[PDB]
Image 1: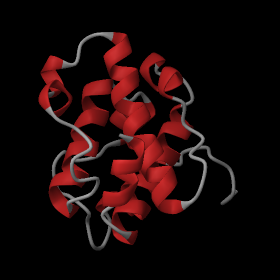
Image 2: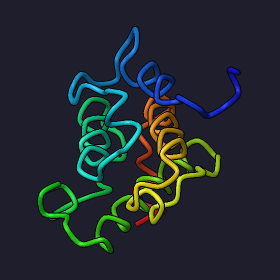
Image 3: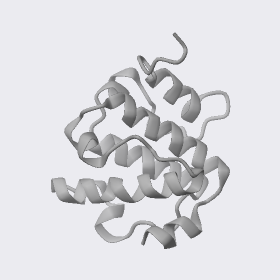
Length: 134
């Protein structure tokens, strides 16, 4: 039912690209949200940052450049940052773990992270959380 995490990519799409979209690009789809590649997740975090100003100053240099992030360790570090900032802004432990994400595992938890990202960027810019995480 409505509590199960099955197909919660539908809630992701409604949270980020519903009636009042957080961002327009990239277009979210069931395909991408069921098996989320790192580059797509980088696109979505970047798109939220660009559309709302969320987490100002969190990233710079190669972290800003999706094609520059190729190493598993770098991917994990990038995700760890935004997950901590979202968690701090909301005061909730995000269930998504960076190593699971990078491996393509628990995609329903990756979707919870994305939904939480959506909720956090509408709560505030997270500027102080960023300075705390850094």
